[PDB]
Image (tube, coloured by chain):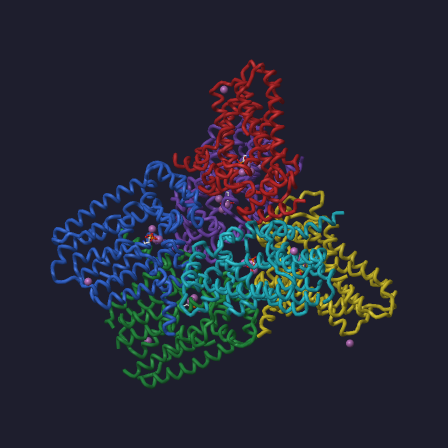
Chain colours: A cyan, B yellow, C red, D purple, E blue, F green
Amino acid sequence: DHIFFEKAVLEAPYDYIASMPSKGVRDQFIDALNDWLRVPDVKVGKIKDAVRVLHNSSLLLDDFQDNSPLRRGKPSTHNIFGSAQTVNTATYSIIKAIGQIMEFSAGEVQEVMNSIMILFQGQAMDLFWTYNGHVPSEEEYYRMIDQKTGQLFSIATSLLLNAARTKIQSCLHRLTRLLGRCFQIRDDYQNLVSADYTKQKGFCEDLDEGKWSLALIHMIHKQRSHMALLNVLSTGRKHGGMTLEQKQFVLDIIEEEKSLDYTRSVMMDLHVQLRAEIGRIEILLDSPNPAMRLLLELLRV
Amino acid sequence: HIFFEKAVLEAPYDYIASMPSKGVRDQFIDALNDWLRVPDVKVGKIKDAVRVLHNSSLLLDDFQDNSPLRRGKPSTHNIFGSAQTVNTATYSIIKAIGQIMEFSAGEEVMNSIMILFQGQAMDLFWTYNGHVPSEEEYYRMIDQKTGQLFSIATSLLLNAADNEIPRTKIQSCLHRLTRLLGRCFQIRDDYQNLVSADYTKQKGFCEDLDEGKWSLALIHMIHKQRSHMALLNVLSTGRKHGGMTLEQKQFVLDIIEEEKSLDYTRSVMMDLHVQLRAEIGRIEILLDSPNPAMRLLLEL
Amino acid sequence: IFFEKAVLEAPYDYIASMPSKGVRDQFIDALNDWLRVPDVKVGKIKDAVRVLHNSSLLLDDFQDNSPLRRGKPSTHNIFGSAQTVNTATYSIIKAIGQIMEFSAGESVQEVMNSIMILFQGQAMDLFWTYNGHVPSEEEYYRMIDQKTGQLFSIATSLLLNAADNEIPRTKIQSCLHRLTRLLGRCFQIRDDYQNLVSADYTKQKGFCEDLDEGKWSLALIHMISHMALLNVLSTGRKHGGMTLEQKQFVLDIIEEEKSLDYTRSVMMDLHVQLRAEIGRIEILLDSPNPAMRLLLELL
Amino acid sequence: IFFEKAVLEAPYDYIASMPSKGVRDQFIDALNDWLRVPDVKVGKIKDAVRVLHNSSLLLDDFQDNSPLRRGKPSTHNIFGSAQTVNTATYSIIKAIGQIMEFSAGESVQEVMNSIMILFQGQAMDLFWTYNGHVPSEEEYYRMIDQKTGQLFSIATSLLLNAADNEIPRTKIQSCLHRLTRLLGRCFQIRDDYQNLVSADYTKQKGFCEDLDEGKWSLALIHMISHMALLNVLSTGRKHGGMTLEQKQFVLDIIEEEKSLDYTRSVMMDLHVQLRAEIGRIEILLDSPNPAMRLLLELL
Amino acid sequence: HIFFEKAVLEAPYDYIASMPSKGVRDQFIDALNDWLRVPDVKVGKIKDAVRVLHNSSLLLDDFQDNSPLRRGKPSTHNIFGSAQTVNTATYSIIKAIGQIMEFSAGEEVMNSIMILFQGQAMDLFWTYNGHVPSEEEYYRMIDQKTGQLFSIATSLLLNAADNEIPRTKIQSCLHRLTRLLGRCFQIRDDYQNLVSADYTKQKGFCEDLDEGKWSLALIHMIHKQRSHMALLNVLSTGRKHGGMTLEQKQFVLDIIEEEKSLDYTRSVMMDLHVQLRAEIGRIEILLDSPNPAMRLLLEL
Amino acid sequence: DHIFFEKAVLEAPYDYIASMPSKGVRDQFIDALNDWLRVPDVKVGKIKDAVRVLHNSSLLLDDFQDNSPLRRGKPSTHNIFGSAQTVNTATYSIIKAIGQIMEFSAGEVQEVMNSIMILFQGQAMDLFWTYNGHVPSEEEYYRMIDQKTGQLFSIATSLLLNAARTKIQSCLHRLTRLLGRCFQIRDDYQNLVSADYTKQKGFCEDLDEGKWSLALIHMIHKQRSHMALLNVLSTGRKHGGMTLEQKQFVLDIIEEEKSLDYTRSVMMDLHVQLRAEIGRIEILLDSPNPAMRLLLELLRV
Ligand SMILES: NCCC(O)(P(=O)(O)O)P(=O)(O)O
Ligand SMILES: NCCC(O)(P(=O)(O)O)P(=O)(O)O
Ligand SMILES: NCCC(O)(P(=O)(O)O)P(=O)(O)O
Ligand SMILES: NCCC(O)(P(=O)(O)O)P(=O)(O)O
Ligand SMILES: NCCC(O)(P(=O)(O)O)P(=O)(O)O
Ligand SMILES: NCCC(O)(P(=O)(O)O)P(=O)(O)O
Ligand SMILES: [Co+2]
Ligand SMILES: [Co+2]
Ligand SMILES: [Co+2]
Ligand SMILES: [Co+2]
Ligand SMILES: [Co+2]
Ligand SMILES: [Co+2]
Ligand SMILES: [Co+2]
Ligand SMILES: [Co+2]
Ligand SMILES: [Co+2]
Ligand SMILES: [Co+2]
Ligand SMILES: [Co+2]
Ligand SMILES: [Co+2]
Ligand SMILES: [Co+2]
Ligand SMILES: [Co+2]
Ligand SMILES: [Co+2]
Ligand SMILES: [Co+2]
Ligand SMILES: [Co+2]
Ligand SMILES: [Co+2]
Ligand SMILES: [Co+2]
Ligand SMILES: [Co+2]
Ligand SMILES: [Co+2]
Ligand SMILES: [Co+2]
Ligand SMILES: [Co+2]
Ligand SMILES: [Co+2]
């Protein structure tokens, strides 16, 4: 009878992150997208649960892969169960999510499998650059984002699309791709700027991780000296993190170079294109979508 | 250079795949196919898929057990780091599943794959929280984390077998076979980790004592009526730290030898060998097809 | 020559200078209102028990790796673990010698036996956290009777052996044993309780010090669907202790399951039994003890 | 119930199972050839002193952070520091209780006082390495008389208090005190010596274990132009201990200055004084002691 | 890009040089030159040379004292690492010496520079081996490691002074001045490290208690007849570890306050202020040239 | 009177390295060079002592800068006295060495000061590349060597030259430069190959340091994959060193690529040029020099 006990052990790390609160964008996008597609409540529920597992599982891996001590102000899962159990649960949960997607969807699965694997191709580059200290170009950065976060929006879109036109499809493609860039570029921006992100992750958590955000990329390829900046980055990699003053030192250089102003420029332009794409769909479709415009608006600053 | 980013993604897999396997996995498929006689191309695809699953499991396991060595060389996460290694490992499992789908469509797997993680879950859970499992829990965990690999390969080969009869006679016997093989190979593995000098050369001296896993020898003497305060506390000391000193490892070995607990493990393995030979025999006669390959695989 | 003595007793003189007090001496004064032991012998008993209690504090702080004691650095963060342990062990021997100096016979072989039970209790405490065993409620209570309640018992045994002739120390026994047992259980449960609730117990020991130690308070034990809490304690065992965020997570689970309420109910029941016990003794000795009842009101 | 006792005594039963022996019991047998104490009481004295000596080994190994004892892991690398210290302190109390069980009067207050001097000696030992003070030869010798020579004194005090009636335990005193003092000084100096020279003392404790501890052997003290040696000891204090290469460097300086020879000369002089002392006692008791002279030949 | 490798070499110097000095060093040279009146160009060269020496000394000292903060910002070796920082520091000292040679030729320096290291040697030696120095040893060490900087600048300015007389009257007085200035500034520095909240903002809370240096306050109360077992042992505990906890630092402060040992340091500083004003006075009259700048420099 | 005690404290770290044994090449080169120049015994003694201090001081810094636990089988100086005292003594000793050079030499000093500073320019690049993980080109590597080790030979040469022609000078320049490259390239080679270097420094000490030797440089810029090789190097930098198996893994890749064969090729060609330069001088001068040819021969394999 204690087969239930074994299941609880296996899914304990998953039940942890899924329990905090943490959500927002994911569920909102599915709801907003469905205000257009009008997919049955039962089918969107099956899609929601699968995407949630998929998203939460990648968070389990990401926090471990990025060595993040905090998620949503609480300890990250691998600081509760340890990295070994967390990774084991996460990998299992992904397979479980794929099985669920198989159960209500035909094949094509052979399209979702492909896109799920693209997510890993995206993570691969992100982790590769961080680990070996290679600064990517701005375009490589965008391509990486399209794969690791943009593809995540695409998956939820493809699922809802297959449960509902024709030309409308190649417009949602432009939507999810632009949306993916908005999310990540904001996420990297807010990590260094916002004080909520400071409370839900720690002060400049990305600088401990050593990820290459758009601000750093822009000023690294910006032709001036930066002997100091280059060396603290190396110092951080050698110590596995930075002190509060070191992070502040990085921010001040960023401020002095106005590289965050560039990031703000890209985000505003992205919102312009996304506004246009949304209205393009609302016109091409029956009626407008305040839910999608809300989500877009939640993504500025 | 679209080729470059895939190379980065699959670099940790190519590393572990470039090492000498020992080919236990491949030898079994070959032996099983001496009975089922599936065409070489279909067999090759199944071999490739299972090889990817197995190697990916080793990627994860070495990191999870914090093993410094794999086949005498540094473990994969001591090349690419934990993050990269885990990422491709999960990806490669997805990829293998995708490969399996392309030539099969059915039907157990993937589902049986989820049982692997169920087995690992218990293995990792006990080790992390220091809970000593019973012999039955130990066996059940092994059926899930190890025996299932064999089950996977069999089902794949079985579903690809010709209409040359029966798939009804064999299935009961084949399940008995893969399960017995799974137990013995893991029990042998946990046994050899402490006594074999080749394993010392491949994994380091008594690597499982660093990992802190619960092998049959330890389990047997702990649930004994004799007191083992020292033994219990060294194991806890090893988990508190990153592992054990050589003297701490040697101390455990002395306790084991003093109580001949490895001899109990030898007895269990021999008894499993007997049942294995019996099971192979029932099939060799029922199909009128002797299998020197399976009996040769047993030679371990 | 005094220098050698000052070096040996420096770690003791450190904790002894701390304000860590307010229960041990008040219990002796409260009990002596009954036993009416001469003030001089009460002084020696107070001194001896003070040395013992301080010595156990030296050991426990080291053994639980507590960084703070009464808001100041713990003794082994001043003198190191080696000097602290050596001084502590010496101080225990010194106290016993003092006890021997004013009491003989089976009184000594009773206190000696009683002191050894303290270590028996500490052993189970230390053994459980080190090997990651979650104790039952009964195991926990028995552990408390040995390591905490026995300290009260020592003080009473000393006082009773020096009691006035107008007092039947044979009728009174077992009633006093029932008292100290309840009192020690009430004190320790409150101690484990307060460590997770208060400040003091965040100002004096740091935030949730028991969770760094990996101590098994009554709240924690009552719970162990509780999978996440088991693992973080294990994570706390593998790491040097818990992060501020990890400790807060434990509190949330306790709060959600209202484990704080359970221990609160247990201590109120102990308050009831204690009042009933003091009453029986008050009738038996034909003497009211407002001090004991006053001491009881410490929650 | 036995389980609780087994847990408490597990760290003691660990060192007690080790072959760490060959001097303590031989001294008792040698001395008893003179004192002719009944075999039964000698047994209890042997048991009590054995518990004390083992308990001091538990503490010292932890306090000096020694990884190895008799080729096997030290006790605190089996049970952890907390359990080891608690058991050790308990075992000391237990032994004293045993001593109390067959001896009364000022005999106890003598052993109690003698045990406290052991801690006084350990205190100076621990205090010096922790605060980086290089002791003089006299300070070192006095430290030895307290922490080592006193152990012999305890055994003799017990045996003398149980001596046969045909023996004048008043004439004999001070001669025995002179003996134990010399013997303890000879034993400890040899102990500090052997730790840097031998194997055993590389097989039993690891290579130059005293240099990890930061112990002040007679060789080291005799030297402190010696600037480089001072700093590596400091480096050894800041780090967890010394590397294999660092220990070897210390040996080279010792060898170059022939510090090994000095301690060798000191111990030969101690051999002379010891023979003179045994002789005086042999005349005074009209009884030869080939055992003591046999025990003496341990170099 | 021959320019690039020099930029790499001087990058750690440019970092520390880009910070707000406080200009005590420059204020002294200006004040001294109100008397000696050396042309601006020759004064500028001397300022530049001394500035390089001083900054290079801070490069070395911050690493040697393992200080995490310098003027509120991370210390240089927490940017470029210990290796690079030390390399340019030694180089910059050579460079400064080369600069000094180009406009002088003589004559004390460099020689006086070697006394700086002699002072640092004792400072580092006592701290590393935990030896408590006497008040006299403490003063002598300070004359060498701090007072000599002032001596260097004076000799340079003195050798560049015009034939407008005397260089014989002043030298005795100027040596008395630079030496008094050196003691007071270091004693003030060690004082302010424990009590000034601005120093907490620039270096962290009680940084010297992390370094484990021997300030006058600690030295005074240690060589006292009262016992200080606790105080002594915390300091040793701090050296055993990387530094002290906040409670350990606060504990030391409480002992200091309880014994008013900082008041003794205040008395010494005031007495040095008195002698300084006296020495400035003897010179202001002997040259018939009052120096509001020197007296204003004293305001600290 | 205890002014001598303060001096002992200051020079204790210097007296340590100077005492072991460790020498060889330095004294041999000065003797071999003087078999030509015939400079008085008193003057060459003054030159020897100064160069020894200079060389030993740089070793004090180098071991600390490279985090080397061992020198000549014994603990490095900063593992006896600590990094702080070692660096303080080293810097002082360099200034002391400069003063000594000033005392027997005119100015031009203004030539020796310049060359001493070049040594630091060389070290600067070596430490910069190691710390920030930048692989230099082969020519940058050679230029760096000319500055940090080749210039050291040049200093001893300039000193002896100024105490003694005309055209002979611009031949010694080619000698010291070639000699500098021979020494360092061999030193980097022997670090990974020789078992004496394994005993006098530890197994593959350079792989812990993370320096960029010619073998690594050659195969890094050699166009093939090397995903594994690139990542262990990063792993080493993140851990502050490598395990025995990791170093062996690096050696095997080096072996597989025959990059050490290339290093052997460069060394043999260097010996060819050096043989030619030596004979060129022996002819241009009075008589041959077996001492210099010996030293050259001590530098192969
Ligand atoms: N997308 C989830 C992961 C992140 O967004 P998060 O900020 O860690 O949630 P990352 O910054 O790692 O890309
Ligand atoms: N189960 C595959 C991994 C093992 O067999 P391996 O010995 O690590 O290959 P484990 O002993 O960890 O179970
Ligand atoms: N028993 C006295 C020691 C304690 O009360 P304290 O918390 O150390 O005061 P514990 O809770 O550790 O038992
Ligand atoms: N005094 C018994 C303990 C010793 O002899 P040991 O070396 O621990 O046996 P020490 O040398 O530490 O004093
Ligand atoms: N002496 C210059 C450096 C100092 O003044 P600083 O306070 O570190 O600038 P120290 O206190 O180390 O002496
Ligand atoms: N030249 C002295 C320094 C070296 O040669 P060494 O091998 O450390 O002596 P490096 O390898 O650091 O260049
Ligand atoms: Co809707
Ligand atoms: Co992340
Ligand atoms: Co991430
Ligand atoms: Co992010
Ligand atoms: Co074929
Ligand atoms: Co494994
Ligand atoms: Co495993
Ligand atoms: Co295994
Ligand atoms: Co009263
Ligand atoms: Co406690
Ligand atoms: Co406790
Ligand atoms: Co408590
Ligand atoms: Co006998
Ligand atoms: Co010892
Ligand atoms: Co000792
Ligand atoms: Co010893
Ligand atoms: Co002007
Ligand atoms: Co400083
Ligand atoms: Co300083
Ligand atoms: Co300062
Ligand atoms: Co010659
Ligand atoms: Co080097
Ligand atoms: Co170097
Ligand atoms: Co080298």
How many labels were placed on the picture?
0
- Residue B266 quadrant: bottom right
Residue toward you, A63 or D151: A63
Residue toward you, E138 or D97: E138
Q: Position of residue F234 (x, y in %)?
A: 52, 65
Q: Is residue C168 above or below residue B26?
A: above
- Residue B224 quadrant: top right
Q: Position of residue F14 (x, y in %)?
A: 35, 60
Q: Position of residue E184 (x, y in %)?
A: 26, 48
Q: Is residue D47 above or below residue E30?
A: above
Q: Is residue E294 left or right of residue A102?
A: left
Residue toward you, D155 or F221: F221
Residue toward you, A217 or C4: A217
Which residue reaches farthest bottom? Answer: F283
Q: Position of residue B181 (x, y in %)?
A: 76, 60
- Residue E221 quadrant: top left
Do we see residue B155 in this rendering? yes
Q: Is residue F297 above or below residue E145?
A: below
Q: Is residue C127 above or below residue B80?
A: above
